[PDB]
Image: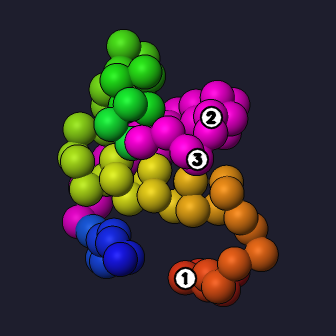
Amino acid sequence: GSSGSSGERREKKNKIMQAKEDFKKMMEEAKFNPRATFSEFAAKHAKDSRFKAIEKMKDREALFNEFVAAARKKEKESGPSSG
């Protein structure tokens, strides 16, 4: 089945952006395999201070789910944002 979040509550600070960046970027560099599970990935890159920034389980599962969702295949039925 599908999962994820819809409409989060950001604060009046540049904390989220910063983190999200280090996270999304940190993973992009790792170029890990989609076969692995979120749990493993988390622990694998848990020591990474930046990674620690993302505690909100939902946030991790979400950011990860999307990352792997695209990593495996790009030409798939997906279109959350137009841009």
Q: Is residue 30 visible?
A: yes
Q: Disc 2 marks which residue?
A: 32
Q: Nearer the viewer, residue 68 or 80?
A: 68
Alpha carbons under labels 3 and 2: distance apart: 7 Å
**Residue at disc 3, secondary structure:** loop
Q: Position of residue 66 (x, y in %)?
A: 52, 61
Determine whether, in the image, residue 38 is placed left or right of residue 74. Answer: left
Q: What's the amino acid at mark 3?
A: Pro
- What's the residue at 23%, 66% (across, down)? 9
Q: Position of residue 30 (x, y in %)?
A: 64, 29
Q: What's the amino acid at mark 1?
A: Pro
Alpha carbons under labels 3 and 1: distance apart: 20 Å
Q: Disc 3 marks which residue?
A: 34
Chain part drawn in magenta:
9-37
Q: Nearer the viewer, residue 27 or 22?
A: 27
Image disc number at residue 80 = 1
Q: Earlier in the sequence, mark 2 or mark 1?
A: 2
- What's the residue at 74%, 68% (across, down)? 74
- Whether 19 is drawn above or below 48: the answer is below
For this orientation, the residue located farthest to the top is 47
Within 10 Å of disc 2 (Cα), the crowding (few <14, some 14-19, many 20+) is few
